[PDB]
Image (tube, rainbow over all chains, first blue to last red; front, side):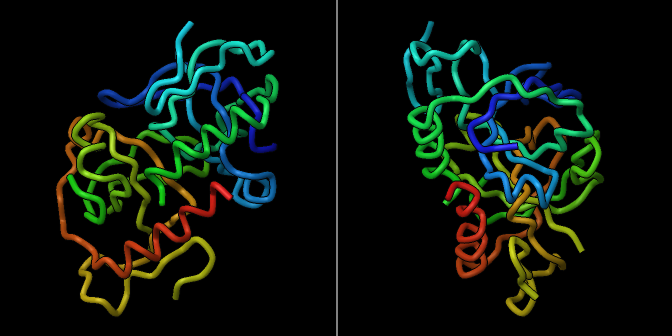
Length: 107
Length: 105
């Protein structure tokens, strides 16, 4: 599993304001990391918006998944245990914008 | 809720190899972010620094073990009933950010 892939996966159960539901998530970590840990770091996709703050729009880039990437909510998940399913990849431009947002808070 | 604080909190329920239990976690995101979102990003503490694991030892921290810088998670600290324990020295926080940052390389 590569950085930049969108996977459909259940994030439940959750507490409080935590992002809920089965939804697309974007893989942040690279293949080697994902292979060794079996615990990729992902950010969730939620619902035609413009990029603003931690929310990066997926509109107009040629992919099937719609909405925005919530770069403020990274989570380490056991994709295999949760039964995630690979959907597609995002263009490197989107991935780099996401990495840029995460860089402001995880470094 | 500041970057560098260790809080004791229930992480459950989680799946598979994800960390579980009620354990110490280290807050990675800054106070303003934590206030606005109510959803700090934390890395868990589990029982020498090696790879993504940063040792808490030798620097006056009461919490023992290693910080798993490879396992960030966004949690609602308040909803889970987290309790603030202590704050790590900046040297430790800088080592943690150093390792954590590499997930973005």
